[PDB]
Length: 247
Ligand SMILES: [Mg+2]
Picture (cartoon, rainbow, N blue to C red):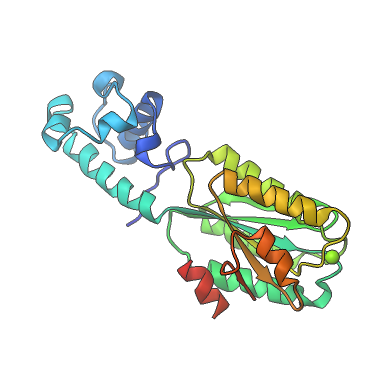
């Protein structure tokens, strides 16, 4: 249901290392007030920990083990529902008064993904890219980020490449194992200069990092432009909140 899985362990246990298994034993010892667990109990990586039976956890950890085994089974279920969302919001002068629709789309979509493993990140761009909310799962920090999204004044030009770059850097910091990273862009496709060339180039970098690029058209949007940023035409939509919740 709800596991207080910290950083460096948010990834799937199959992608863990030997130091991550030790960090998992140190976290579980204080989270569940377990007996002093020796660090040399599970001298193996994450892939080898998934092959052991529950009787092996009892042998290596007589006091716990059964708790460490069942906790690993719940963490595997948390990783299946784990997902990283990135909201790329266009705060340029092109959206103007339509920024209320961008805020309502993010607010209504944030009220649905209430899972503890669901982490959100707010990145607005408009002649400058600034990550308002870093990637976190704390609902209090997300509610703080939502209020700051309303504090945004639509001023600047459209430069999606700089906004998608900050999203890919967070995906790069999470790594390719965080394939559940999803980028949700809320723009109007009103690009100028070589930005159409850099927006499609930066989008391919997101695809190389194992991320899905979803585009949300606001007011008027060049469909041919957003289909090149997104993976396909199906991932482009102006209902739409349910479509984002389904995929
Ligand atoms: Mg603009």
